[PDB]
Image (cartoon, grey):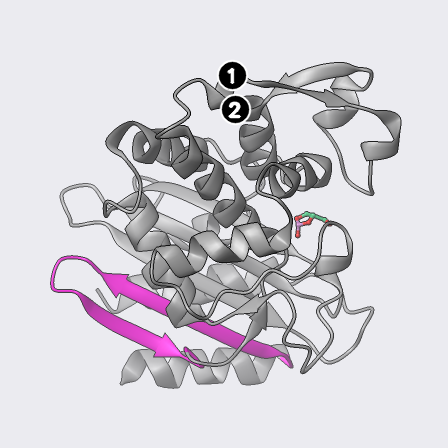
Amino acid sequence: SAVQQKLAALEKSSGGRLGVALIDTADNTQVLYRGDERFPMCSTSKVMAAAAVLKQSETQKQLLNQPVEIKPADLVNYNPIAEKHVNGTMTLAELSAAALQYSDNTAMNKLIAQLGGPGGVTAFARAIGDETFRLDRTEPTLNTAIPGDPRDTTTPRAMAQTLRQLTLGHALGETQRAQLVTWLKGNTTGAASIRAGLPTSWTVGDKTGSGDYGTTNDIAVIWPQGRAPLVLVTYFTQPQQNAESRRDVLASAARIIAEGL
Ligand SMILES: *[B@@]1([O])O[C][C]([C][O])O1
């Protein structure tokens, strides 16, 4: 199609490897570019950790209000929110919000621990039918994004389908679903990624991700005004270990997708 030619050309101009999956919920059609290739998830994995805790709260009604201590030893490389609560507590809700809306790495590690380790996050994925997602490490080492390394990867197709189920489907209870959507809509790190390639009137909830090898990711649910929502996953990684982020590629891919609709 025209879109796949344009995405292929974008990829060629960028010098990296681009993965795209769009689901149009109107007719359930899919647009895929390298949709079945594995990409390092980096912080896009945090959506799975938050959703897993949300699933736990369906039975543990008060779980999200459970205070969790933030100790200096818990601090890793990027903790914009946890930093503000060292030697104090944050609720599991506040940690989920920090993981999603500020990409706090310490918060992500507390969610993993709540789930009993990375195997606990991966288990939730299998439970909702995602047999591709795999989380193997904690922050910050899950961001190494080494070419060919299957650890901490998923495919654009698998992630799009799963993000659809979590936000638009019923993988989560109604209250949990609404909370996840509210959290994603309030993401603060995505202004230069998918959002930048779309009309300003469209409502977007997304989770960005970055890591080594110039890995630059964004996954988003999109509510166009008057139109059925869309799910868009954009994964991008590069061959140089110290390559710079390329959020512009994510915006250009989003723009090319928006043109085809
Ligand atoms: B994710 O990828 O987003 C930011 C942090 C930096 O380690 O992780």
Q: Pointer 2: what residue? A: 93
Return the residue nearer the eye: 208 or 38: 38
**Rendered residue at 64%/49% (across/down):** 117
Return the residue nearer the eye: 110 or 15: 110
Which residue type carries mark 2?
A: Ala
**Rendered residue at 56%/18% (across/down):** 66
Percent across and percent down for residue 244 are: 75, 64
- Residue 65 got which mark? 1
**Rendered residue at 34%/31% (across/down):** 176
Q: Tell me where residue 167 sits by quadrant.
A: top left
Principal SS element in the magenta part? strand
The answer to whether residue 48 of the structure is visible from this angle is yes
Q: Tell me where residue 114 sits by quadrant.
A: top right
Q: Tell me where residue 86 sits by quadrant.
A: top right
Disc 2 residue crowd, few under 14, some 14–19, many 20+, Cα 10 Å: some
Q: Is residue 174 above or below residue 213?
A: above
Residue 19 is a magenta residue: yes
> Which residue extends farthest right?
73
Marks 2 and 1 sit apart, C-alpha to C-alpha, by: 6 Å
Disc 1 residue crowd, few under 14, some 14–19, many 20+, Cα 10 Å: few
Question: The N terminus lies in which quarter of the figure?
Answer: bottom left
- 107 relative position to 125: left or right: right
Percent across and percent down for residue 134 are: 55, 65
Question: The C terminus lies in which quarter of the figure?
Answer: bottom left
Q: Is residue 18 above or below residue 79?
A: below
Q: Are marks 2 and 1 in contact (CB under 8 Å)?
A: yes
- Residue 112 got which mark? none
Magenta span: 15-35
